[PDB]
Amino acid sequence: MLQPKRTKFRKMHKGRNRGLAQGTDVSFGSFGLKAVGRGRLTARQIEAARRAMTRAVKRQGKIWIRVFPDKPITEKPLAVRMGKGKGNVEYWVALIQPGKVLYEMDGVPEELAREAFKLAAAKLPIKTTFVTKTVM
Amino acid sequence: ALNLQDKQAIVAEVSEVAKGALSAVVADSRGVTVDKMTELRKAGREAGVYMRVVRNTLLRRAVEGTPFECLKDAFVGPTLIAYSMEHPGAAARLFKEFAKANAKFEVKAAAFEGELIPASQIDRLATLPT
Amino acid sequence: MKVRASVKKLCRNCKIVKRDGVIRVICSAEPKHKQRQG
Amino acid sequence: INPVNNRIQDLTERSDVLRGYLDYDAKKERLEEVNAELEQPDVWNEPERAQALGKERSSLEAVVDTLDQMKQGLEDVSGLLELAVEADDEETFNEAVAELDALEEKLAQLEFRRMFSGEYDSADCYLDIQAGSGGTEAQDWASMLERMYLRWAESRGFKTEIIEESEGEVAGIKSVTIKISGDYAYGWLRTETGVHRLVRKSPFDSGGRRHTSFSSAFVYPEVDDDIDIEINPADLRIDVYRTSGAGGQHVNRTESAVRITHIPTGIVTQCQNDRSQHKNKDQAMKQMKAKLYELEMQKKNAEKQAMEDNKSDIGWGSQIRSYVLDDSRIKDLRTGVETRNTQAVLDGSLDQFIEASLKAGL
Amino acid sequence: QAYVKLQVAAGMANPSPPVGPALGQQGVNIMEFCKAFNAKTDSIEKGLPIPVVITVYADRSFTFVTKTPPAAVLLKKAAGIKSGSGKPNKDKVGKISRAQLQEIAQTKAADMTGADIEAMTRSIEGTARSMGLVV
RNA sequence: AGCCAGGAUGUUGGCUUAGAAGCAGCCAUCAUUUAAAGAAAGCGUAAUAGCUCACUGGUCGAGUCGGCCUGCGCGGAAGAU
Ligand SMILES: [Mg+2]
Ligand SMILES: [Mg+2]
Ligand SMILES: [Zn+2]
């Protein structure tokens, strides 16, 4: 489960998740799973996806996780009223914009890679798509 | 397979026909692979690798290469059949071999048509140079 | 009869057919395989 | 080639010993009957039986086959030994030597499997030595035993570690726990569990009478401490309801109280300490977990109790060796092997007993 | 008609433990097959398995035609090793030269389907590779 | 797309296994007779056997296959007078 080792700050503002993503292209691998939807992947979710895809690829070929859950999300404890400071950090998310290459993969046949990505995709909350290495 | 390979195959077949005048038939409408293998091995024993049973007797495959040489072979087309081109020796004895094979379990599929070399009938010709 | 939200061809013999506006997997081979969207 | 000859001589002897321990003829007979059963076509109609019979067969066959291989190989080597000696052909000699080595290895393998067939035999052990009813003498005896064990363990290459030592007020030790790490440590030591009989004139007695003092050894393997598994919400029923007495308007309405129930076992935990239902559930959950743990412990204990009860049933048979120092003779009661070198045994020559015990399977 | 290849070594007269019910499944008796095997054996060699056609006729008197012994055992014999399959590409257990393989090929020519001995040799090489031994 | 035929050889590849013969796995994944036939995709077996499939030959005689892009719809879709 991915999480920042150190932090500058323990809690964080909600913020907004508008715009298009920057990590848009398949950089390292041959194939990628590009996020079509807007949302936020938790660390847990990402880990699950990784687990799904590694198994599918049967420990053959490399996987990159292009996303990182660097934003802490707070949850107020149950049966607790609305005041009294900010809630405690429960889980960590990567905020996802459309265009985000989430995962990358190489050293695999194409069909197999596709299959793996499909398997992964069902674990993630956002709508996603298979993408390829492009010259330029 | 793409067009080019098919064309090449056709050319090869044509070349084979040009090389060898005598020919005979066989058919596997109920034929064991082992028998076929044995038959193939016979050819090897006799002479070179040249001879193939060439199952490609479609309406526009061997029948398309028929206008080049032995023009009567077009009517053979619309049936399950397998040709056998014979290169060395003037009228070899592989024609009756097929008949023999048929006799030893093949359930009369080809009906030993002959391929007409001295313009022969449907019936066999034992009269062959030895 | 597996009534599901996702119906899929589970083998070669599985065929997807639509009957009175309902998606259905019917299979000639395996009776287990036959499905309905619901 | 004299050492080679000696080795050859040894090997036949050990093969014979192995046969004796195995009871080879009976095994062969069993193999034969099983084989006969096998070929009868009616036996494969019953599937459960047949697979079991097959399983039985194979091991027996292996045992038999290896045995005569050993008989034959040795003979071959002996035949070739002459050639090596008189004719002086070197390559042939070398070949013979190689064959012998192979045969030896095979023998070892067979003996290994005969010995260390148990589940925990490869693992390391905790040897526990306890002094008997005697007093000072008993304590001394226990100490002696401990020393002997240490010497033995050092000898073969095991790592000893004195975990706990209760020291005797006058001399020796009241009790000791020794962790013995190494390859097949428990398998080598498991036979030494039991009561040891010292017979000697007591140096601590003022009268100087000849005492029969006892001290127990107890070898148990270091089991891997299994993680206490998280119970599934599928196995659980969570009831929520109103509290007893309560006391107010909000209390009458609110269902804070939690009853967690284990479906497979039938244990219940109630909690209604907190106002918050969630908190109660958490507390109740904890309680349930604790209860489960307790149950697990109880079950473990019960099984353990059965085991010793069975062990108790043997009674006087727990006495495994008799160390007579006056007449100068050690006897293993289980096997029947005797030696007059008592001092040597004390120093740590237990291999002669232990190996035989292992071969026996007791 | 009920033809199946299932037998152990030629020297082992009447295969009781391994084959058993498989040989005596049909109407033909246990003793006959064994006798036939014995008869076959004396002309060539003992110790190796040899496969044979089991055409079980209604008259009981079966027609049988022998085949060449399995290739794997021959390969093993050539090697001088017993087991060489456990993790072959991770670590090479045994190794054979091409000439030896070629030699092996020639002897089996009667039962092998083909005219070219080179073909046979390459088949044998492939078999060896499969087994675990690197050429 | 139907339909008729073949769908083999070394070979049951070895091992480890109780047994393993394409199909418990672990691993190599070759070559052969060549029209084509995986040391095997599914069913099947105590395991073999057996039944399919891949690819291919024959018949038949015009379009066909499955991705992408989008428009509109379908299921997913249960509550209390
Ligand atoms: Mg940004
Ligand atoms: Mg809708
Ligand atoms: Zn189906």
Image (spheres, coloured by chain):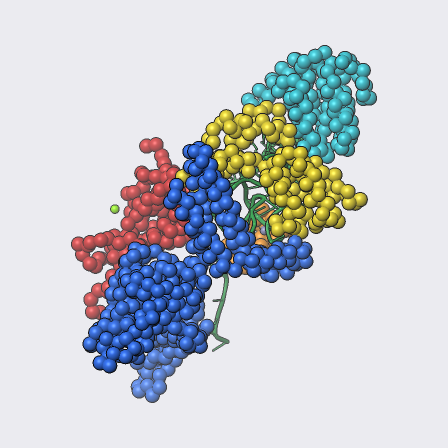
Chain colours: A red, B cyan, C orange, D blue, E yellow, F green
In the image, residue D306 above or below residue D149: below
Residue positioned 28% across, 43% down in the render: A22
Going by the image, does C10 lie left or right of D310? Answer: right
The single residue placed furthest to the left in the displayed view is A8
Q: Quadrant of the C terminus of chain A?
A: top left
Q: Name the one closer to the observer, F12 or E18.
A: E18
Q: Can see residue D4?
A: yes
Q: Position of residue D325 (x, y in %)?
A: 31, 70
Q: Name the one closer to the observer, D337 or D106.
A: D337
Residue positioned 39% across, 73% down in the render: D319
Q: Quadrant of the N terminus of chain A?
A: bottom left
Q: Position of residue D119 (x, y in %)?
A: 42, 61
The single residue placed furthest to the top in the displayed view is B90
Going by the image, does F22 lie left or right of B125? Answer: left
Tally the marks. Answer: 0
In the image, residue A136 above or below residue B113: below
Q: Position of residue B120 (x, y in %)?
A: 80, 16
Q: Name the one closer to the observer, D113 or E127.
A: D113
In the image, residue B10 above or below residue B1: above
Residue positioned 80% across, 18% down in the render: B126
Going by the image, does D48 lie left or right of E54? Answer: left
Q: Position of residue C37 (x, y in %)?
A: 54, 57
Residue positioned 69% across, 34% down in the render: B32
Please identify the quarter of the rendering in which residue D258 is found. bottom left
Going by the image, does A20 lie left or right of B4? Answer: left
Q: Can see residue D239?
A: no
Please identify the quarter of the rendering in which residue D168 is found. bottom left
